[PDB]
Length: 287
Length: 122
Ligand SMILES: Nc1ncnc2c1ncn2[C@@H]1O[C@H](CSCC[C@H](N)C(=O)O)[C@@H](O)[C@H]1O
Ligand SMILES: [Cl-]
Ligand SMILES: [Cl-]
Ligand SMILES: [Mg+2]
Ligand code: NA
Ligand code: NA
Ligand SMILES: [Zn+2]
Ligand SMILES: [Zn+2]
Image (cartoon, rainbow over all chains, first blue to last red; front, top):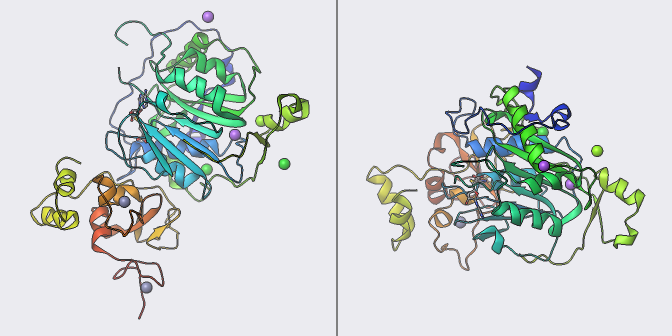
């Protein structure tokens, strides 16, 4: 299949435009995965397909890129996702990761503890989150916890032009996060081909604008997401994992400028929208 | 990793402890992070990105380091680790025990390959 070759499947605009009622999801998140190649961890495969998908988007890639990775630790005590990010990102990109529990990492810095304790003055070019809480005994409402911190972190600490990829599932999601997706030049819900039988997806926001481009209702969009997953079964595929020749993120040398609010006009928003500009300071990073 | 890590962490000589543990029939440390790669790399031992050739696997460095995995001091002069933040290439025949491989082997200082494996020097 043509779809089988892709690193995964993005939620079609047709489904984003709906106003669906919230239903239960007909998918299970755990299963014996027949597509993961031998000796490869699910999360290496998953993050590899995520990065392959991010390669198709207009990500800003400054010369001195700043990337922060939340929920980077596993119960294995290692950081498979971080290792993939380090493989993907330009050499000497600042990569900081974080998790509630202790783990060993290939990141430049590793912060242990609840994400809410993570403080930094500096802004970031890319935010990746794999945060998830097993914890849904009754209703499926918008979840707070780390999502509340994440929305604040994006609003305060993501550079204009920056991008995000945040893991969600049927039950692990947040209405304000979805709303915030409308503050990006483009957004989608992306399902990796290696984990396609799960309700997991990454909410990807490309090129942050710091203001609404469209009005997203979070409860409605999650219902739209569930409806799409319920009505479009995706067969597991690891096809994309067998050609790694073009994997690393392209070195774009994206301009970084510190501009005042009043300097950010029409032509600047246009550059931001096209993945051609990052707006933030270039001070020393302290996390 | 279930016993092996503590066993070595609470030994006077953690590397010797791992060897003894293996000699007694214990399973090598698991969950070393194997990368997806082209297998058309330089074949050097420790690199900035995955550089496996056709005879090697590439692993995330920190996950293949005994001292990182046991959360103990490195024996290096200060506290520096040669593996963490980098990728280590390991002969496919030896890929079952990446931590053991790095403990038992040494990188040639001229060609940058593993002595007794990829290194062909005089
Ligand atoms: N409130 C919170 N703060 C920080 N980390 C959290 C959190 N809630 C969940 N997490 C983390 O989210 C992770 C889900 S598993 C993440 C897998 C990891 N990305 C990998 O590559 O293997 C767990 O490690 C858990 O510690
Ligand atoms: Cl790619
Ligand atoms: Cl330009
Ligand atoms: Mg565009
Ligand atoms: Na970007
Ligand atoms: Na509503
Ligand atoms: Zn180490
Ligand atoms: Zn040599």
